[PDB]
Length: 302
Length: 306
Ligand SMILES: C=C(C)CCOP(=O)(O)OP(=O)(O)O
Image (cartoon, rainbow over all chains, first blue to last red; front, side):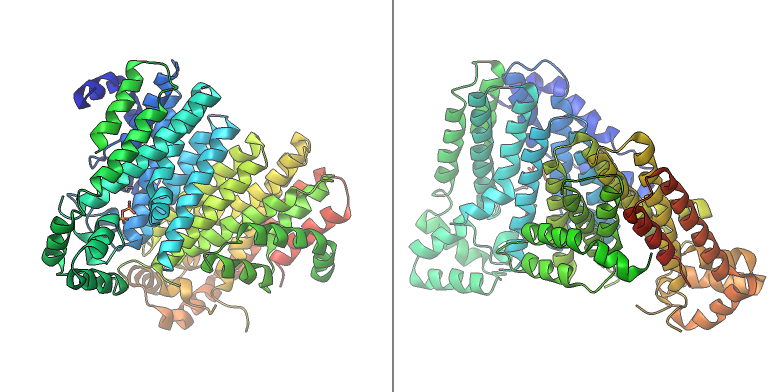
């Protein structure tokens, strides 16, 4: 299945997920709603929620509570973006100025706490202690990972950073609809694998398909492959740039190093094998359009 | 009841609290690890987690999960403090304060859910959301001399009182106390939380004879500064109006203090706090007379004494 067939299949729900989000920017404190609208109305992508809504429909759910969990997951994602931009001192989040550049760090961090606690209130309103423990652990696991990276297998770094919230989204959505243990492990895995592939792609896309990863010598897979399989000269450069935590102005020779050792595609067929495990793990679920839709997002990812 | 006796009466539960704290802040990250020892070593009063354990025993709690509520309440306080350290382009550190604060907050939420009580999750969620809302309201009030005392009161209740209220109430909910008792604990937290912040705001201008002038220098309008402004002479009301708008007016502490003493702003605030404290003690009268209720009362007295 492809994009528009999914944008239309899931059109009604996602519209509700969208109203559910904006509905909670309720504060009497205007700065909260301002900064909120500013960041959630910048395009986004809505995959995590789309995965949430799909996971539910795929297991027979016919209610509208999956619309609320998908919405709170987006708020969570939103909150980590707000804090990440303050931490990474970013002034650009594709297109416009980050919330911090436009509102200030304080507001950005404080509004993200509002948004995160509100999502938490939304979960408690769902009354499932299991969804609460799964979700609270994933977010904490993310938070801890970010602290580690701050004071310093890179598949461990992205699992925590990205894959884990995907895992939670699909799984918790399943628990909420009242899925089966086999359907829960299935959905949970789809999320973990699609999340890993989502991130791998992302890192490979930072190298102009921006440029931030190298600028600060991030140990991404694309960069790590080039190092090992390139010339000792290209290899030395990449290595010191990482030890230096700075690869500014080293983009061209770096590319040449990749476009020669096939590091940029050795990374795509790494996310391609993760996207696979994802579609496989969905064997369990009942053959519904909702599933072939999930199967869709998997292929589209890479 | 004296502070010395309050500390001994709760020494055991506070050891339970510290244990809970170290178990949770235990991590290989090293930065989170250091934070554990620093908290359980603090020479501070640590009144918030203390109100949580006291609350539970006051209503007959015989288990020991009240110690976890005490621990998560201090994590919440600690987390809000870290985030309050974030500096704008008015430029530990931003990265550290934000990320460590995030680890702490998220861990408290984990601890909340471990208690297995949706009702407790209902009350804490709101509180942290309200604390967060109140923090942003305070951000907006910086350099604004025209906030009503309603706004200001909503601020102290929001950023301080609400946690005290939640601590007290959740311990009672956990102890399965009765509605009347819960509402009494609940109110006691609110009022004491309020008194606690009013004493704090006025002390920011005097006492001990960090340091006075901070709130003034930050252009942060607190009850006493606002009161002097609305009750002082026009010249004084203009200087205080300018000090809030411009900031960096720590050098105006003396003149401001004179404006305050002139209309009784400081005493007027202490008065209002002592009044909030009595109201907190009134709420507790609906609880069985016990040594723990005596301790809760002592804390209300100590919070406003001079
Ligand atoms: C690795 C992550 C967290 C960034 C990409 O995810 P998203 O595609 O969901 O980000 P946005 O669309 O919201 O900018």
